Amino acid sequence: KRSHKHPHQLSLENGAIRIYKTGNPHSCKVKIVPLDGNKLFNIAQRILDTNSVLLTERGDHIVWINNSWKF
Amino acid sequence: FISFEDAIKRVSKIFINSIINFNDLDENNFTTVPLVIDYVTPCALCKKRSHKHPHQLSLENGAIRIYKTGNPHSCKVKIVPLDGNKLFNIAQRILDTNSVLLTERGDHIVWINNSWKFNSEEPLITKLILSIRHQLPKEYSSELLCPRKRKTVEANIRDMLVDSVETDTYPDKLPFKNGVLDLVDGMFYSGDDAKKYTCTVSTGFKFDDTKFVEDSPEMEELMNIINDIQPLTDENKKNRELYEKTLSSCLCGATKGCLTF
Amino acid sequence: DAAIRGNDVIFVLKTIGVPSACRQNEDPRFVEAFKCDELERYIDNNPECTLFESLRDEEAYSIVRIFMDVDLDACLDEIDYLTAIQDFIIEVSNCVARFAFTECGAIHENVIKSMRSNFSLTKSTNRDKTSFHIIFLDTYTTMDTLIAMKRTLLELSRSSENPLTRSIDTAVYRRKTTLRVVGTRKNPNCDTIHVMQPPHDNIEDYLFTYVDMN
Amino acid sequence: MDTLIAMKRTLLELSRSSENPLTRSIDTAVYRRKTTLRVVGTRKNPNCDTIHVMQPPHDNIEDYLFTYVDMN
Ligand SMILES: Nc1ncnc2c1ncn2[C@@H]1O[C@H](COP(=O)(O)OP(=O)(O)OP(=O)(O)O)[C@@H](O)[C@H]1O
Ligand SMILES: [Zn+2]
Image 1 (cartoon, rainbow over the protein chains, first blue to last red):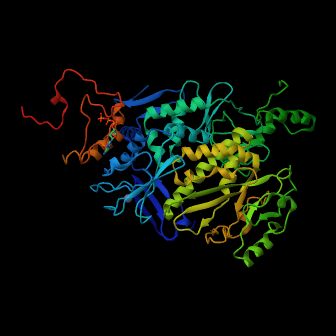
Image 2 (image 1 turned 90 degrees about the horizontal axis):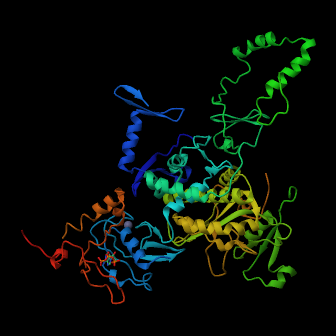
């Protein structure tokens, strides 16, 4: 569409954030974002975001510890 | 279906509050008597506060639908199934997406990151299950965050695959890591358009139309090298006519019946 | 195959429970064969008439569009309706494409693109119910294919959780199927009819026998 | 009492969060008004032949009654 003249809006329901366009909702698409998950999965995501473990083209994993890359 | 007591169990877990008429539900009158719950915490359907009308349960299509009498918009509609396993349904949906296939060699090919990948010693199925969770409803995405459930879904998917499929059947398509180009038209298909051609190999370098320009300075200096190697002379034209035949023959993926020196 | 052969005549009935022999006899009081414009005129000039759409002879021409019916005895808000219809479209497209690839030997991506490109929906005038007929315009198949796919559709309806998906009725896929014409009175003493959709303002987009292979 | 009716949400969310094997098989609606619990050795119905099996090292009746309060 073009510039989405009607402002969007946010809502929360059953542990999910819903995004929908005000005015005529049929002119846009409703989007869903789950703001929930496991603690261990969140920890793994944070560790991955730290960017300390990588995968090589030969099927090996390299980690970054003690200021050194080791596999 | 299942045991009635388990149905009451699931219904009572759905309602975070307790009901007063628990002793009044029986196997033959649970669709008629109104349901009134204790009022200490707002109902799970809608936040609101202290719903002013009793609820009711209906049985349709092997499921129980909960609806609040009075204002239809007051409380949200909830459907409880009583038939099967959630993991089996998730596996069925993943198969319906048509992203994992079985080849005649006994290995499983997986569509990840706009490409077909296969590994003979690594379970790519779990990675596919984790990656595909964004194209599933809300109630299914939460279950895929646990490794054990992912292994169970992988086992179900592996059990479900019986027949094999053929791969790399089109010799006129050149694959890449970001798509496939057609040798008869030059048009480059990317994303889902490239899923039609089951190509398990790639050139290794991604396609880019920015350098795919005839009117470029890099192109002009290549005719000098090609003339140095193969002069454009009449007595050698047959050789020239042969020279391009082998050079262009490397693109296709069909069997060749000749040897070149 | 058909190629030049493209259905343009519209076979229409006038009352449920048509007598058997009069159908072969083709009595004008129950059986009509029209085109788009004169059918529109016939449904416009007479507002109290009841019309039902069906095929005449599937022994020589039995290719139709994909059609489904949904009916739920509850009211939903606009946003929940949109979310449910989106998930329903995705799930139905995946299931139908998987069935076509597994049995019919078609191509998954072509089926998905065709069924998700164009589709026509209706609404019911009743406030307390949510019912609609969905027509996939750019997808064509034989009636026996629908008969075979009925079992998979029933399994999907049982397995799913979306309220719209649980309401799919598979009984419509059987011998001598019939459908209600959009914007037509159902019963002589019932005012509940079906209305249009702003995307599609043409009658020919709401018939499942009108075939035109572009 | 009123504590028990308030942690029901807490234990249900812990069970939903924790993935321990038997934790997925707890009951939440048991905490309610006029809660009734089956006494050990008493069948639900004469037709039912299921009874509670006594478990050492506790053998006395007061060891399995939540309505009994003693200060030691
Ligand atoms: N009023 C009620 N509110 C909530 N749950 C109830 C109510 N009445 C019965 N139940 C449930 O119905 C079931 C009947 O007990 P059942 O024999 O199935 O198992 P139990 O609770 O392990 O048994 P026991 O009585 O030996 O403790 C239980 O799950 C109980 O929590
Ligand atoms: Zn509510």
